[PDB]
Amino acid sequence: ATQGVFTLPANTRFGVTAFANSSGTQTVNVLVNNETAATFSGQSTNNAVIGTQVLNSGSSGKVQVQVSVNGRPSDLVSAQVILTNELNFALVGSEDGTDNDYNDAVVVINWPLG
Amino acid sequence: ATQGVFTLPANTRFGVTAFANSSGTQTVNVLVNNETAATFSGQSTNNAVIGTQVLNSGSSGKVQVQVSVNGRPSDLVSAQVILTNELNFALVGSEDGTDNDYNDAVVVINWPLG
Amino acid sequence: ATQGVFTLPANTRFGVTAFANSSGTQTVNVLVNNETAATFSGQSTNNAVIGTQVLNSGSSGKVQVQVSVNGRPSDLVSAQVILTNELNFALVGSEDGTDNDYNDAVVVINWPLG
Amino acid sequence: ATQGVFTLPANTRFGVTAFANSSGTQTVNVLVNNETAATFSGQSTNNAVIGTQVLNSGSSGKVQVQVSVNGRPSDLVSAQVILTNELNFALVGSEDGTDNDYNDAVVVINWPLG
Ligand SMILES: C[C@@H]1O[C@@H](O)[C@@H](O)[C@H](O)[C@@H]1O
Ligand SMILES: C[C@@H]1O[C@@H](O)[C@@H](O)[C@H](O)[C@@H]1O
Ligand SMILES: C[C@@H]1O[C@@H](O)[C@@H](O)[C@H](O)[C@@H]1O
Ligand SMILES: C[C@@H]1O[C@@H](O)[C@@H](O)[C@H](O)[C@@H]1O
Ligand SMILES: [Ca+2]
Ligand SMILES: [Ca+2]
Ligand SMILES: [Ca+2]
Ligand SMILES: [Ca+2]
Ligand SMILES: [Ca+2]
Ligand SMILES: [Ca+2]
Ligand SMILES: [Ca+2]
Ligand SMILES: [Ca+2]
């Protein structure tokens, strides 16, 4: 199944934050309506916050997360959780290697803000 | 129901990151085995990271998140999610007022690291 | 925080399934637009499916779960999870006593159907 | 990523319930310790329960769900959710065709029981 693609409310701010846990340098791309809106990168095995930003979901609300390590795409897992019918989290893990810890880059998207 | 309390595997590193979305100054306490292990405090209406730290779950694995604003405990909502039987997220939202957006302090706990 | 209340897309079929795990007889009421649309009752300590039914979310999409044991409301806990940006689960646990296993009546709502 | 595989606590009784939403007949196998422990089959486009059973997770706790339709394995999506640090759901959706509704067989695993 497709992973790392979420439908957000239209025209709404959301936070996106990325964490690294790998010997490889991660590159995280955040796409909004199929255009690159943010790119984060770093190298840490201790959960460094390699980027955080507030973005707007635009007219379609379509948000996609892509992760790659020196050009090769990582395998993604994802889900969305809603607490008390209001608070949303979209969660992404990714695997760049063979140990299947799926933490090599971790992306958290949260809304609403403010 | 009790919220904000999580059982982690013993002696496991985990990341904790807190965001703020409120006019009020948020104080986030992270307790490991009933003892304060980290405290974050900050104010933002734009999802600013008010703290991030790597902690160890200790011998009991009990982790608890408290949130208060000017000494008043916020109402909490929480859940844990596990992706591909390996990647864990413990998620907390909190409400300090009346609009019930439950984002006034948001806390994300993730493990494993490394 | 409020629990057991979910907003579904309007005029959408959904499944609702209740399980029991308690010495007390559980009564599960499912409200659609503030009106009782289904009710199930039974006693089991071995996860009996005390009822399963297909309902329609109506014009408002507002779905609420209520659980009581001998007229006393149980304490509820809930969340919603979305898989591959399509498949929705709304999950309810409830506690009728003091052991806080929150399985005394368990309710699963899933959509889409068909 | 691997989907439909879950590590339960050893020697624990859990419930498993399967629903169908497809023109195809679903066969759902539940494996404990890499052997088939239960098999459900049926056909419905209305979310019928095609089986429900209580099983033991055994010495290793490893549980796996597989779904076959028309002779071929369906693509799976899954996650695990824990509410109030005590109530566990392992959730599986599956796709036997081309419309990607991932509801063609839906499997819910819940524990603890009792
Ligand atoms: C240090 C190692 O770096 C890569 O091999 C990752 O895939 C591993 O999960 C681990 O983080
Ligand atoms: C600016 C406002 O500040 C407090 O009143 C919060 O409870 C609101 O959710 C909002 O963030
Ligand atoms: C058999 C017991 O019945 C009630 O006391 C429940 O609250 C308990 O959780 C347990 O199921
Ligand atoms: C009736 C249809 O039957 C199969 O084609 C399923 O894959 C579809 O999702 C739909 O349920
Ligand atoms: Ca890895
Ligand atoms: Ca790693
Ligand atoms: Ca608020
Ligand atoms: Ca707020
Ligand atoms: Ca109980
Ligand atoms: Ca019980
Ligand atoms: Ca299908
Ligand atoms: Ca279907």
Image: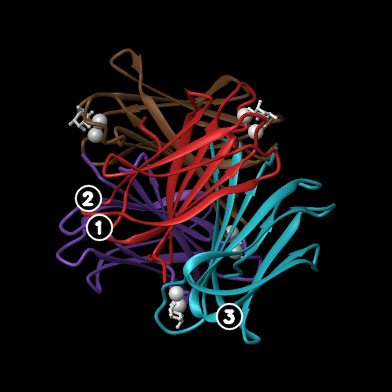
Chain colours: A red, B cyan, C purple, D brown
Where is residue A7 shown, x and y percent of the image?
Answer: 30, 48
CB atoms of marks 1 and 3 within 8 Å: no
User: Is label 3 on the same chain as label 2?
Assistant: no
Chain under disc 2: A
Residue drawn at (29%, 32%), measured in percent from left and top?
D104
Where is residue C43 shown, x and y percent of the image?
Answer: 48, 59
Disc 2 marks a residue whose amino acid type is Ser
Disc 1 marks a residue whose amino acid type is Ala
Q: Which mark is residue A60?
A: 2
Q: Residues within 10 Å of mark 2 (few under 14, many from 20)?
A: few
Image-based side of A76 in relation to C14, left or right: right
Where is residue C24 shown, x and y percent of the image?
Answer: 53, 66
| Residue at the top extreme, as displayed | D71
Disc 2 residue lies near ligand 11 with CB under 8 A: no
Q: Which mark is residue A10?
A: 1
First reached walking from the N terminus: tag 2 or tag 1: 1
The part of the image, by quadrant, that contains residue A114 is bottom left
CB atoms of marks 2 and 1 within 8 Å: yes
Residue drawn at (48%, 23%), measured in percent from left and top?
A71
Disc 3 marks a residue whose amino acid type is Thr
CB atoms of marks 3 and 2 within 8 Å: no
Would you place residue C32 above or below residue D30 in this image? below
Would you place residue A76 above or below residue B104 in this image? above
Which residue position is annotated with label 3? Answer: B25
User: Is label 2 on the same chain as label 1?
Assistant: yes
- Could you tell me which secondary element the residue under label 3 belongs to? strand
Q: Residues within 10 Å of mark 1 (few under 14, many from 20)?
A: few
- Residue D27 appearing in the image: yes
